[PDB]
Image (cartoon, helix red, strand yellow):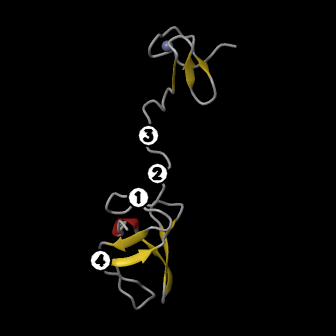
Amino acid sequence: MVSTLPPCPQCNSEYTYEDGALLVCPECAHEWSPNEAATASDDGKVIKDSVGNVLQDGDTITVIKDLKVKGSSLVVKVGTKVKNIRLVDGDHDIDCKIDGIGAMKLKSEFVRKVGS
Ligand SMILES: [Zn+2]
């Protein structure tokens, strides 16, 4: 019947309760979350480039380094435009399909969101 939750960092009265996914203090009329008040970057497994930017499933990318292709005759050059990518589960994973050779996987650390 009693809350095992922390007090209120504003009242310390301890008359705090849990209303769903956080703690609400009915005293000072302010809800707060113990750890989430600090907040962190979650949903961050989205594929990020060496530019420090985040891509979108369908966005246009461009390798910013000289990358070879092992099974294909193609060599990936700084400016290799591959659009409409697929964001895979791992942040180190850009799935892309390339007219001609086929589908390929790209190292996030070697690619970049074009900006278009
Ligand atoms: Zn309070």
What label sits on residue 54 in the rendered view? 1
First of labels 4, 3 by sequence position: 3
Q: Residues within 10 Å of mark 1 (few under 14, many from 20)?
A: some
First of labels 4, 2 by sequence position: 2
Q: Residue furthest top?
A: 13
Task: Answer left or right for 97 relative to 54.
Answer: right
What is the CA distance from the residue labelled 3 to the residue labelled 2?
Answer: 10 Å
Task: Answer left or right for 57 relative to 76.
Answer: right
Image quarter where the N terminus lies is top right
Query: Mark 2 or mark 1: which is in front?
Result: 1
> Which residue bears the numbered disc 4?
78
> Which residue bears the numbered disc 3?
40
Task: Answer left or right for 64 relative to 87.
Answer: left
Residue beneath the point at 48% across and 30% down: 35
Q: Which of the pair 4/84 is nearer the observer?
A: 84
Disc 1 marks which amino acid? Val
What is the CA distance from the residue labelled 3 to the residue labelled 1?
Answer: 16 Å
What label sits on residue 44 in the rendered view? 2
